[PDB]
Image (tube, rainbow, N blue to C red; front, side):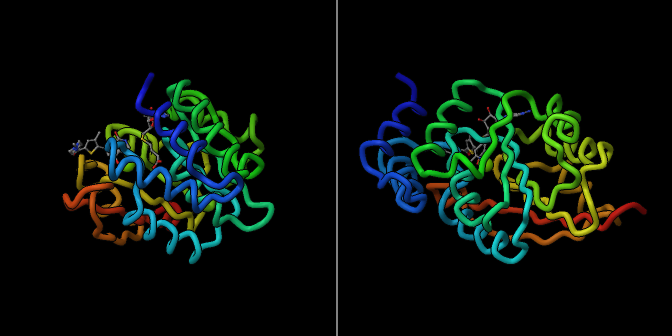
Length: 214
Ligand SMILES: Cc1cc(C(=O)N2CCN(C)CC2)sc1-c1cc(O)c2nc[nH]c(=O)c2c1
Ligand SMILES: Nc1ncnc2c1ncn2[C@@H]1O[C@H](CSCC[C@H](N)C(=O)O)[C@@H](O)[C@H]1O
Ligand SMILES: [Mg+2]
């Protein structure tokens, strides 16, 4: 028995199959009541929703799936024929995410890439026929926000207007990523102040929109 297995079991036992919203509510509730977990959460999640609806991205890359929360959260808002790719380094997590998605009936929108973002990113074009990404959600590991951003730019995966949206720019924090995007002419940055999931510690998401080469 693992915490993530408990979360998936709670969903299967409580959420309406095929209804993404009830799946989100089931997760939020269990982690609000029984056991904190690092899902992006409902407060930050509403900000994500608002940004998704603005940009209506056809191709979203997620870094870090975990239990599938934000994948569910995002894919439920995708237009028909839009796809989300999510990268997960931990097999136990990737398979729980696959199940969470299957239960919400979003499996056909979502493709889980198993492995480390740094290894998978260079393989997107060949193995998944990706041209450029419309949106990227950074939410794996703070140390990799900056390295992986440079990777994406280098692998030609960013176009003018690509939206990078980063979670935890305040807690646990991503100082170097923040300083880089805020300092670079290649990004237009906006900060959304929210709260750490299932808590009232202050956190935020950063939107950094790629402007193209300088
Ligand atoms: C693991 C962890 C602990 C945090 C914290 O301050 N505390 C936790 C424990 N509780 C009890 C107090 C407060 S915040 C956080 C966290 C939150 C995310 O949203 C993350 N997203 C992606 N990848 C991460 O590593 C990630 C970690
Ligand atoms: N370098 C990396 N490449 C791919 N996945 C990574 C990674 N570093 C950490 N991860 C994974 O990213 C997850 C961070 S928590 C992700 C939560 C998710 N975005 C949500 O809001 O629901 C963890 O499951 C961790 O195993
Ligand atoms: Mg997070």
